[PDB]
Image (cartoon, rainbow over all chains, first blue to last red; front, side, top):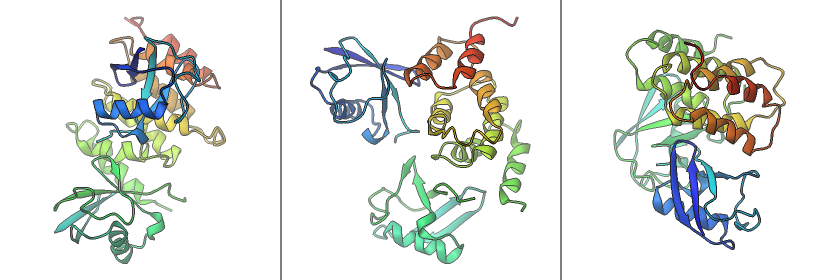
Amino acid sequence: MQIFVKTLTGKTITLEVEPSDTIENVKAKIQDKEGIPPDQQRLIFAGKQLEDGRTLSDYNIQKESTLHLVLRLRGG
Amino acid sequence: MQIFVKTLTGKTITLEVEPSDTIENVKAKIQDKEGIPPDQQRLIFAGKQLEDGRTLSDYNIQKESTLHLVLRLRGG
Amino acid sequence: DTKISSAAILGLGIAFAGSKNDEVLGLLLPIAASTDLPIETAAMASLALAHVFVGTCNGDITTSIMDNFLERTAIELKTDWVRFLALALGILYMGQGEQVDDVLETISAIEHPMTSAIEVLVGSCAYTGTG
């Protein structure tokens, strides 16, 4: 499912994931896109904050869903 | 090489280290200069916290590098 | 107990309208971004950035200021600083691109605590409405 990831700063990233995909996996994909280390990406959805391990299914996150992302200070 | 350490005040400490030098070793040198104990130091560079054991080479810390000396949650 | 912090904020204090230096955020931000650091001193610092960078604003400034916002313990509510903190998240923006709109959306993303004060306040200020 083509999901969207909106960053607090101001940038939307399109990532093709699945319902069984693990949050940790998503973070990895983001790192491959930008350069923000996984241990520096706070994902949040309509519900609350998403933790590692869990899957995009334990939140009902469907397709075209905008996931908020708050990085901990400049990655680099 | 000659590296510098900027304090959260305005003073910059210059210390002669090597690329193989271990962070823990550096912190020790700082303790001998000032008076802050290792278990009370947080070296950051390019927005990246340095972990003990590692060396100044595992962070691409060349010479004339201004290491940001931050206090890990100062007691007082 | 004249902490050295005074001598620090002092110098910068004069650099306020200086000419935009990288020492401002290079010292203030950390004191209020590193991870925790005293909220008090950090409070007055946060304001310094607002008034100063009142014109041009940046995300990094908010993001960092946000990280600390969450780290809140709701236990130190004893000391006064919620005012400056709030006014900050406000004066910061002023309309440019549903910027604030996104902010309020985040606060709600993580439940709805006593942040109400911010919601309402920041909620009022947003689009054009001050001439």
